[PDB]
Length: 147
Length: 144
Image 1 (cartoon, rainbow over the protein chains, first blue to last red):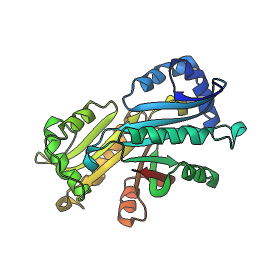
Image 2 (image 1 turned 90 degrees about the horizontal axis):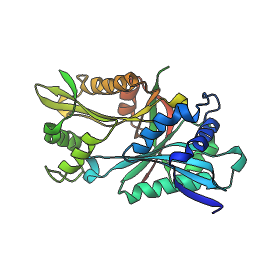
Image 3 (image 1 turned 30 degrees about the vertical axis):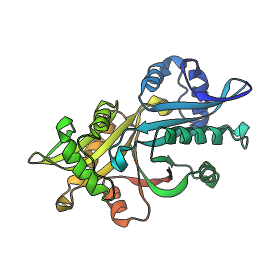
């Protein structure tokens, strides 16, 4: 079909790399070959799913869901959502909302008690976008980085 | 005072710690509950760290190292479920376990280590700043 939503798989790597280049324009442009080993590890990782929205078969948005086993809250898992990206060039078409909301729904279907997300974006429009996906800005994020 | 990854025997001690963390949570055996603990021990990239005092787990933090394609395909990490037994707080156990988790992540070439905590909690935020964390990510959550 013309518009779809699915988990990523083998052949999706080139398209995903293009999205991640949009996400971080200063990142080096990894080739499909350079990225193959980590992509395979991701596909093999228990509880990790990369979701894509596609338009005419091209990935146009993505979000990664991480479901984590857990002993708190009646031993119910929790989840994070990471590396969400959409395109300039598809702004306001809803593909980001589709993929993030799908990831949330997938986590809740897996009995996660909460889904969390951290964003470093300065842009209030990004924050509003996450609220429109059902997130509430009621947690405080912390980060430490290294070179 | 020793830092190590959790193992099969640590379930009661971890359950006690998690009960301290969330006093409202329903109790768990052993099992239950042994099934999930088994899943966590089996989960790739996940480590439950404990600080032990003469054998007994007195503090814990969970490290999640996640494979990733951005930033030249460097991994990143989350830290979760950080707690120290009340009687042992202020002795540096919590700081030590958190710092150990950060160092483990950085040793695996993670470019960042992140965590989410409750809003407007001055003691907790000062604690994380004291471990080297910067409050420069905006946190979102949805619950069911």
